């Protein structure tokens, strides 16, 4: 999926 | 200790191109010729409209020191469609990593970006190029349909690389799977068989690779460094890779099996941020026939003598045991901020004594931070922790970046075909690479006897030359025998120095002299044939008269030391032999005055 | 004939605040900045600091691949996929030098926008170093306990992480602000803890880590490698900054370690600390201390933990 | 060397039924019991109007040696329509192949014929049945729409069969595609999930099967025999099959990946008409964990010592290298026309010595051609080419057909739960099957010391009991230690027999005698504990007076032999342990007289 | 006492010889495959006799010829078990095919050439399914059945095998459920091989031994590419020879005479039995040449032979296919 | 259709 710095946003 | 620092071969490259960022040898075979290899990651190329596309040059050993780039790919940025760039070869850092095995050459570009066939993106999947004779193929195992960061989009394949004993490639890509990193291995026979220029994501049958894991492993950098060696006795080389940001940044080093990529052993650093795993190497360092693991931690800081912390670095040495265990010993740096342990180069038997040796670099140490390299010799018990040689960087900072002498290096190849492994060192900070040649080693068996040793003052046997006086004499016989491996002549010129009653000082009176000189000292220019039998010279010494000195108790020591005339034993290229540093170049005996009795 | 340390088994003893808010403005911090907005700091802190000031700066990460997306649409706005009002990424930006006017800090924060990048770890040590060496831009007061509060929720990039981006030149540890902006964020690699610690100590700067998530334990396990620094976990329910900074300051002053420097080409400094009850001692205001030093032979300092004696 | 021949368990079926043509163990694990499975291809049944349909009997090991027939299919020939018979189950040779895995049994009738759904034909597609405890189903993958010799019409599916590690079947059919042969592998989970007694050609989702190829491969017989083993390091068992007529009758053996049926490796015989490939087997023989391949060539003839040919048969051993190619040795036969290599049965670790073993039969060799089996043990270096044990057939030919003892055999199952794999042997020619049990192996270390070893006649120290005399004495000490693996008694009993001055014969005076007996021999029944500490017994001997013998030069040898009390070491069933193969029957020491 | 053989002698480094008698009397047996694939070759076998005697008079000293046919085993899966095709394997092609059979003996060795001419003309064609044919079963029966065929005592026994395809092997019969090895005896109840459905084919070893024990030399008359198959098997069958029938036919007479010439020029030697333990033979030619024992000597006609045999640590020494066995014993 | 009956078909 989308992890990292932009993960919380989504 | 036998690396020739007098006349090293120096190679230069275009300014600012980081010439020397990566080095290696190249022995193509099918001919009696050899060459060097050097990487220039930031080098400007003729490729159409590409800036600093990187380049790898081939520097020749024969006479001149001239290098020519290797045209791996003269094309530009291919187009997936009209005005739709498929690749981005600018600032790709081609040549950041180099590696050669006989005829095959493998260079990579960790910062090569591509578009993906599915969307207009710029992803650094990294690509590599492989040449064999007249064939040249591209190899981007991370250039796949598995895109984006959660896939292989940022893998930067080729970051580190290595060959195997059976022609398998091993490739690191620390960006895969949100920087969990990845390892990939492919049969060289498949990289060429399945190559297709119109296909961008090639699939190979016999491929081994690590798979994505849980998110906790994010930011581990698996594939940051790589080495190979057998660690289960199967004969198949297994895969060793550093994982610097692993285990909450303690760092780790994974070992996978080379036949099914199944985990074998883990190493775990012991200090956070020490970057345990920046470098790794494998080689039998103690003649046991089992590869030994060397791991670098350039940013480790030890509690010094004053209970204070200071960054020095640290290498860990592990010896493979027959049981499968590892006898691990550590080794800290010497200078602060020198980044000791940045590079670790196996050397083979640098001195041909029976055990392999290893170089370890501290690229930011020495005078003015010009870089240093340390040579360590191996033994049956392990690695001798005191270095036998130190290579000091010669170039001062050019503009901004330090010289970085020792950041890369490669050994284990005898290029001048003299019998001893040679060494290459690189300093990309000034765009330089150096080839240090291994000097042959002469081993000397010296012997010294003094008979009689209990001297009797009233036993006056010999008469002084010419006169009729009589003195208490005794013989001093020194012997010299030597041989060596490699290119040498059949006769050696030594320089023997004997001294009688060494304990006595300048002002003190000397009690024993030589019969034919009447002096404590005796020089000799002896000349033995190489590998001959013991050649000896017999001398006659005597004592001063009974009434010339009072001390009869202090022993009378007899010291010998032998030097070797290096300038004359040179070979066809001026490479001078050196004396085996293992043995002491001096030996001492003793005789005493006899007192009273019955 | 004096300073604030006495003197200026042989033992020794000892006898104005500037805070700098160095905040991570990465995308993951979108919920913590909104709580950083709000005045009370001075309310609780006025009685103990005996007058104080505070600056403000922000950091994200190095603005190069692969730490950010080099795609034109998001290279300047890393939130293009979510069309969010994100400001451009940056290594470190200095917006407010140390100022005694509190309202300026409140305005500079409220005006702050959010950035974004890719990889979870953020380049914080890069900003911390510049904040320590750049004295003329920040204006660290001479005789004042210099504090640097770092606010983040994730682990930090290390020195050799930069090899991925092709950055291989070590950090030089100098100040590089042409127009209150860190320009070398794309040319020099991150600083090591040793380089960071030494430059932190050389400027008598104590660090306060304001962290939130599970990554708090990460910074906790690093305080042994950074003398003079302290860590504190922000409650995920937020609005706990004021209670943490005061608790961090209290514990920071109770810590009294000692360190050495240089030698006469060969000396032992076998220090042996004794408490009123590791060289420091907590839960000790102007109370006695004592450290026993042993000296030997085979020529120019003894540095207190972040304090202002050769 | 440790197979019990004194009292084996002999099973017998109906006469002329070829009882014993195919044998296997049955270990259900849902019953905590164990049985033997025996095939009777030409046995008569109760199936309505059928002749010699064949049976498979479940022979019980515990208590008497009595067998019962398994009921797979009690129906006769089905009808496709009124007076249009679909099936021809008569003379189908059901039970010609048996192969059991856990509670799952698979029998096949390679001569089953059927009508086909398109034509009044009679073609031998072959069929199989699969029982799993309470449910039994049919499995005929060659009973399909690919009819006629051009297809699977003559496939004879089930000629050879085997199970795999991951619940899959491997079935062979040497008749597919004008006798090119074929291999078929279906998941057992689907052979049960898709079965339907009103559907005659059943579709299987995950089926793997070889594909018809060029006509040059006609008359190849792929699927004549099958074995299983991993040969590419994937964990999944791969398929191995003999192709005896392939390559102009030189014979071949194909290996296919057990995951997509792609060719992996090819073996090839060296001699024409040797029938290289009649039998095959796959097992790790050198403790490396790499399945090694065994191939039989019953009709191979070797240029004998007299420069003349003679048909003895030949097996080829092939060790799987880690590199991936094989290290191959060859092993010939012994007796002429004995068909050495008709059957090859992995045995597991017959002596639990760390390396798996193997048996090899010569059905038509020995005294009066009654069939023999040859037990070969494996080593770290390969297969020890010297047979440690020979099993001889003990039945004269009833009539017409030879007993064929060893034509089929199965092993690697410890049926008596004593920790040692046992062996089943069938001799269909006399309708018999034997269960050979493996005896426990005792390892014995014996010790013998003699001190002093130089004896001084004038050194009279010990006093001879019963007389005022003194004599020159020396000590004789012997020790003993024993251990073994598996089910063994807690204590073993050895009968030691020491003799002094053995180099002398009756009449010649014995020089040294035992102090407390004045005799040259000494007998002791020593009792030590398996796996316990060694047990020693100290003795004392002496020499005769100087004036009682003249020879002082001949050495005084001390000879020891130690039997085992087998009868008492036997277990509840009378199975008595056996001493390890290479254990000395005697150990000797020496002492000499001292002259002047 | 006497020396009543054709080999010198009739009963250590002792030499041995043989007498290459010129103008032998010959007994030929035409054992032909009558499968469907041979449909074109039988029609060519018809008028071979009369000319055979014409060509064979020059080399033979009076001779005879018999005739028999073979197809395959009359069981599944070698034939079709369909009631309409069990007896007529050519039902789909409605051709006048006779029933299949393992082996049939129609004409014992007869010197009346017209009799052979009649027995062949009367011959029909059979058919079956699988390409390989059961020829070895018939060859064996033709060798051991001496009273039915009538092999002459003093006659170099020739057996011409005529086929166009490879042969079934011993263990091929497992497909048919036939697992009892061949016993190698004569099984002709009424000039018909009855055991063709109960005993498996004979192996080459069994076939060779029975051929030698009866002093029978074989001639393979093959046509298609499968000639090379029988050619590559002559190493395993001493006393046999092969010849490629020209696909244009009319080559039987030229092969049998050409094959006979080479057969008489061939003079190998073999051993038999022992005293429970080398017989290091070394054959020598008319021309100085060191020829291995089994090597024989070619291009020999009525000239001397030789070959000293060494014996060291009841036995028989047989010349290849000769009517004379010089036995030796101690 | 191949085998023995192929020539005829
Ligand atoms: C990926 O592939 C690797 C193979 O490269 C595989 O590792 C194997 O794992 C299997 C089981 O998981 C092992 O199989 C077992 O081996 C037992 C004996 O192994 C010992 O002896 C081996 C013999 O080698 C000797 O001889 C050869 C030839 O002379 C020579 O090459 C060797 O140098 C040596 O002289 C030896 O190789 C092996 O070494 C491993 O183990 C030791 C620890 O003892 C370790 O120190 C080594 O570093 C190495 O890892 C070992 O010493 C054998 O007894 C055992 O048999 C039992 O179990 C089987 C069921 O599996 C039963 O059938 C049997 O009856 C016994 O009950 C079993 O066969 C194999 O040895 C490993 N091989 C290696 C090289 O490690 C991985 O599992 C694969 N991973 C995946 C995911 O598939
Ligand atoms: C008075 O002093 C004189 C000398 O000033 C002394 O005469 C010498 O004594 C030495 C003994 O110290 C003799 O040395 C020996 O020579 C013989 C040969 O004759 C050797 O075989 C001897 O054996 C070994 O010596 C070496 C080790 O010591 C070995 O390297 C060597 O290979 C031999 O194995 C030994 O070398 C010397 O020969 C005499 N010389 C003469 C001319 O006599 C005398 O003995 C002293 N007397 C007293 C009373 O002090
Ligand atoms: C060595 O010694 C000899 C003495 O004979 C002298 O002539 C020569 O110059 C010396 N050489 C050196 C290099 O010292
Ligand atoms: C003798 O050699 C040793 C090296 O083993 C060295 O340490 C020592 O200083 C030398 N002594 C003299 C007097 O040169
Ligand atoms: C016997 O054979 C040997 C073969 O080596 C030969 O040398 C010898 O001459 C022969 N005998 C006679 C009598 O010639
Ligand atoms: Ca390995
Ligand atoms: Ca080692
Ligand atoms: Ca060395
Ligand atoms: Ca060299
Ligand atoms: Ca980041
Ligand atoms: Ca497999
Ligand atoms: Ca193996
Ligand atoms: Ca065993
Ligand atoms: Ca058992
Ligand atoms: Ca046929
Ligand atoms: Mg963030
Ligand atoms: Mg035919």
Image (cartoon, coloured by chain):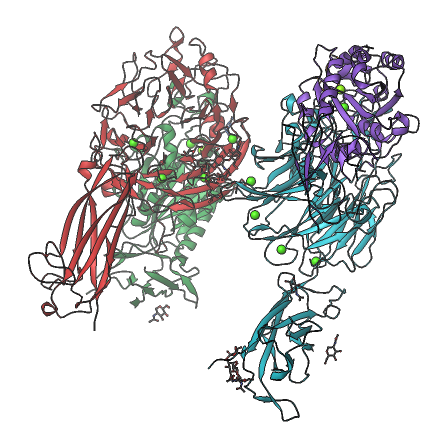
Chain colours: A orange, B cyan, C purple, D red, E green, F blue
The N terminus of chain D - image quarter: top left
**Is B77 positioned to the left or the right of D92 in the image?**
right
Residue C190 visible at all: no
Residue E140 coordinates in the image, percent (x, y):
33, 41
Q: Residue furthest front?
A: C1
Between C264 and D451, which is closer to the camera in this rendering?
A: C264
- Corner quadrant of residue E87: top left
Compared to B522, does D94 lie above or below?
above
The C terminus of chain D - image quarter: bottom left
Residue B212 coordinates in the image, percent (x, y):
64, 24
- Corner quadrant of residue E50: top left
Residue D142 coordinates in the image, percent (x, y):
46, 20
Instruction: Classify the position of ligand 6 by quadrant: top left, top right, bottom left or bottom right.
Output: top right
- Corner quadrant of residue B178: top right
Residue B300 coordinates in the image, percent (x, y):
69, 38
Q: Residue at x 30, y 17 (%)?
A: D70
**Is B505 positioned to the left or the right of D338 in the image?**
right
Compared to C67, does D502 lie above or below?
below
Between B421 and B395, which is closer to the camera in this rendering?
A: B395
């Amino acid at each position: 999926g989308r992890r990292g710095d932009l993960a919380t946003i989504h | 200790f036998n690396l020739d620092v007098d006349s090293p071969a120096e190679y230069s490259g275009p300014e600012g191109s980081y010439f020397g960022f990566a080095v290696d040898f190249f022995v193509p075979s099918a001919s009696s010729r050899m060459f060097l290899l050097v990487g220039a990651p930031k080098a400007n190329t003729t490729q159409p409209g590409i800036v600093e596309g990187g380049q790898v040059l081939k520097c020749d050993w024969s006479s001149t020191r001239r290098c020519q780039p290797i045209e791996f790919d003269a094309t530009g940025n291919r187009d997936y469609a009209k005005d739709d760039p498929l690749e981005f070869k600018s600032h790709q850092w081609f040549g950041a990593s180099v590696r050669s095995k006989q005829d095959k050459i493998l260079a990579c570009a960790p910062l090569y970006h591509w578009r993906t066939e599915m969307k207009q993106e710029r992803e650094p999947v990294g690509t590599c190029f492989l040449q064999d004779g007249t064939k040249t193929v591209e190899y981007a195992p991370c250039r796949s349909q598995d895109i984006d960061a959660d896939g292989q989009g940022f893998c930067q394949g080729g970051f580190s690389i290595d060959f195997t004993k059976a022609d398998r490639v091993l490739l690191g890509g620390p960006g895969s799977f949100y920087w969990q990193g990845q390892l990939i291995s492919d049969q060289v026979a498949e990289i060429v068989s399945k190559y297709d220029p119109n296909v961008y994501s090639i699939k190979y049958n016999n491929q081994l690779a690590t798979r994505t894991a849980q998110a906790i492993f994010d930011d581990s950098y698996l594939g940051y460094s790589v080495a190979v060696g057998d660690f289960n006795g199967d004969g198949i080389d297994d895969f060793v890779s550093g994982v610097p940001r692993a285990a909450r940044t303690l760092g780790m080093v994974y070992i996978y099996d080379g036949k099914n990529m199944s985990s074998l052993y883990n190493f775990t650093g012991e200090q956070m941020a020490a970057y345990f795993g920046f470098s790794v190497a494998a080689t039998d360092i103690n003649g046991d026939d089992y590869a030994d693991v060397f791991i670098g931690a350039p940013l480790f800081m030890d509690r010094g003598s004053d209970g204070k912390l200071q960054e020095v670095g640290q290498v860990s040495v592990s010896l493979q045991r027959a049981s499968g265990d590892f006898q691990t010993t550590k080794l800290n740096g010497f200078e602060v901020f020198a980044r000791f342990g940045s590079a670790i180069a196996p050397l083979g038997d640098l001195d041909q004594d029976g055990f392999n040796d290893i170089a370890i670099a501290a690229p930011y140490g020495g005078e003015d931070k010009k870089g240093i390299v340390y040579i360590f010799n191996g033994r049956s018990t392990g690695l001798n922790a005191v270095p036998s040689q130190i290579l000091e960087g010669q170039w001062a900072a050019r503009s901004g970046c330090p010289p970085s002498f020792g950041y890369s290096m490669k050994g284990a190849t005898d290029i001048d075909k003299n019998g001893y492994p040679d060494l290459i060192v690189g300093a990309f900070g000034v765009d330089r690479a150096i080839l240090y040649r291994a000097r042959p080693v002469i081993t000397v068996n010296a012997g010294l006897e003094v008979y009689p040793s209990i001297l009797n003052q009233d036993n006056k046997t010999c008469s002084l030359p010419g006169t009729a006086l009589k003195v208490s004499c005794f013989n001093v016989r020194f012997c010299l025998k030597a041989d060596g491996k490699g290119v040498l002549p059949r006769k050696l010129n030594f320089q023997v120095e004997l001294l009688l009653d060494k304990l006595k000082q300048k002002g003190a009176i000397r009690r024993a002299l030589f019969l034919y000189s009447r002096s404590p000292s005796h020089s000799k220019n002896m000349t033995i044939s190489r590998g001959g039998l013991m050649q000896c010279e017999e001398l006659i010494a005597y004592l001063r008269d009974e009434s010339e000195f009072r001390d009869k108790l202090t022993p009378i020591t007899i010291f010998m030391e032998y030097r070797l005339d290096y300038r004359t034993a040179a070979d066809t290229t001026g490479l001078q032999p050196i004396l085996n540093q293992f043995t002491p170049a001096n030996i001492s005996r003793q005789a005493h005055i006899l007192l009273t009795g019955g | 004939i004096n300073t604030q340390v006495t003197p200026g088994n042989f033992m020794l003893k000892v006898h104005p605040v500037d805070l700098y808010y160095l905040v991570d403005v990465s995308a993951s911090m979108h919920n913590n900045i909104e709580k950083l907005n709000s005045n009370d700091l001075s309310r609780k802190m006025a009685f103990f600091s005996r007058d104080f000031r505070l600056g403000f700066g922000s950091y994200v990460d190095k603005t190069v691949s692969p730490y950010i997306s080099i795609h034109p649409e998001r290279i300047h706005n890393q939130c293009s996929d979510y069309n969010l009002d994100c400001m451009p990424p940056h290594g470190y930006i200095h917006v407010l030098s140390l100022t005694e006017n509190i309202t300026e800090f409140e305005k500079a924060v409220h005006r702050q926008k959010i950035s974004g990048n890719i990889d979870t770890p953020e380049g914080g040590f890069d900003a911390m170093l510049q904040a320590a060496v750049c004295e003329s831009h920040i204006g660290w007061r001479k005789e004042a306990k210099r504090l640097l509060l770092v606010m983040t929720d994730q682990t930090s990039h290390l020195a050799l992480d930069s090899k991925l981006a092709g950055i291989v030149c070590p950090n030089d540890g100098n100040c590089h602000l042409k127009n209150n902006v860190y320009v070398k964020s794309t040319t020099m690699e991150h600083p090591s803890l040793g380089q960071l610690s030494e430059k932190l100590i050389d400027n008598n700067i104590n660090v306060i880590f304001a962290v939130q998530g599970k990554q708090f334990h990460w910074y906790k396990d690093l305080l042994p490698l950074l003398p003079g620094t302290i860590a504190g976990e922000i409650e995920s329910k937020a609005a706990n900054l004021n209670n943490l900074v005061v608790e961090a300051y209290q514990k920071l002053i109770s810590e009294v370690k000692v360190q050495v420097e240089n030698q006469v080409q060969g000396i032992y400094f076998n220090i042996t600390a004794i408490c009123p009850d590791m060289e420091g001692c907590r839960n000790v205001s102007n109370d006695e201390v004592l450290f026993n030093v042993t000296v030997t032979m085979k020529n120019y300092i003894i540095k207190p933990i972040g304090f202002n004696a050769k």
